[PDB]
Image (tube, rainbow over all chains, first blue to last red; front, side, top):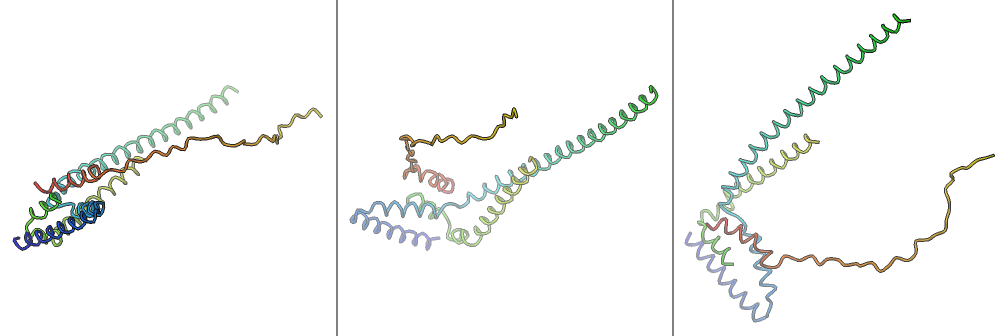
Length: 106
Length: 49
Length: 49
C-alpha cells in the first residue's frame, strides 16, 4: 500500500510538471483533454458491490415479471382458444338446426 | 485530478491489483448480469409483441 | 360511344424554384467541461466514500 501511494505521488508530480509545461506553452486544451481521458479511464471500484446488489434485485424482479407475463399470455391463449372452438361448435349446431327446421317446414 | 487521486490513494495496493485480478472477475460478472438483464428485457418485449 | 374514361392527365405545371428556406441547424450545445465531467465526478465520488 505504501509503495502504491508513493507511485501515485510520483505520477501526480509528473502530472504537475506536465501541467506546468502546458501552461508555459499555454496549451490548456491539452491539459483539459488529459484530465478528461484520465477521468474516463479510472471510473469504478467498490461501487461494484451495491451494483451487484441492485443487479440481483433487478434480475429477480424481472425474471418474476417474465414468468408472470408468460402466465397471463398462456391464460389469454387458452381462454381465447376455448372461446373460438365453442363459437365454432355453436355455429355448426345453429347451421344444423337451421337446415333441420328448413326441411321440416318445406 | 484531486478526485481521481483520492480514488487511487483510497484503495489498498492489494485492492489496486484487485482491480486487475479480482475486480476483473467482479466487473466481468457485472457485465454478465447486465447482459442477462438485457436478454430478459428482450424476452419481455418479444412476449408482449 | 358515350365513354367517359378516367385516363390520367399530363399537365405541364413544373415545381417552380424552391424558396429561401430557413436552414437554421441548431448548434447542439456540446456538454462543457463541468457538464461533461459531472457524471464522472459523481461516479468517482460514489467510490471515494
